[PDB]
Length: 81
Length: 84
DNA sequence: ACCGTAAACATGTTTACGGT
DNA sequence: ACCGTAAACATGTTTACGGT
Image (cartoon, rainbow over all chains, first blue to last red):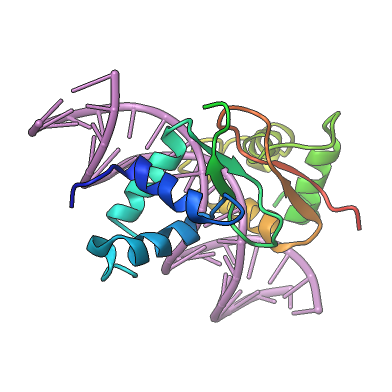
């Protein structure tokens, strides 16, 4: 596929969430459900490595501790960045 | 071979030894290597893979240890004691 | 310089097992 | 029941490289 970039797909996923925040697990399902090229890829390697790479690298994504036991962090858009 | 103290006991004494009563996982490794003689000669990630895995397992298994988001660039979380 | 892809490496989380 | 040990899997963080 082409279209937008990995950093743009994560942003479009976050903007659709009511609380303006999504865990890494939630981003995976949104990509499978919203992007047709990932529709058959709901099973950790490849494009899932690229998503984690983009979240830690780009300053426009911040990591927020989750208020749920055993749950991964919240990923939201950086206000300043 | 370090005594009758458990891993949770060793992690607790390390955390209690800090002024802020909180340490990162990397710092817990340093106290074990620096304070416990049995761990003094196993600082490299070859002889350490064993006990370093046991420490992360103890921090995540027992409710006594809690995780707090760090306040740095990409620093790992703080590990403190559960108020319970 | 940016992006996608790959890989090493660190940090957390659970599940399982044998010994005391 | 508790502990130590080992291991699978997930989640985060860096570094490198070819192509545009």
